[PDB]
Length: 156
Image (cartoon, rainbow, N blue to C red; front, side, top):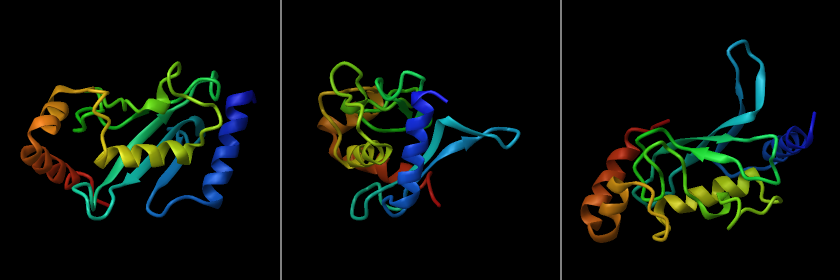
């Protein structure tokens, strides 16, 4: 099946054996029922005691046949509000940078946990959207309002 699909089957097996509470990660189900190992639909829970609490944020992971030598692309929905998320939804996380961050042994769980931390602890060196980044830097009161509001968009 090739290297990528072999690794993704290992990632699936490990995830199903042991993953953090409240997270979801699985290969997408295609229209006819066939599972596609190359695109995973994941859910990252907000941490209790942060403005992300109570939210369950949908994150899609997109793998190529170049994986795991090259990183996946991770996306929240278009319009998602966060300093490090592009208007398209793409997440800017330093381990997803092929040249300046990625290591091929990093697991799906390790990626999802890194993104979870990124929610309440953004990386100020990676501005990716004007809305989220401008509020975050120098307007903490409005930023907080916006994050709390967005968590209500992602229940359950």
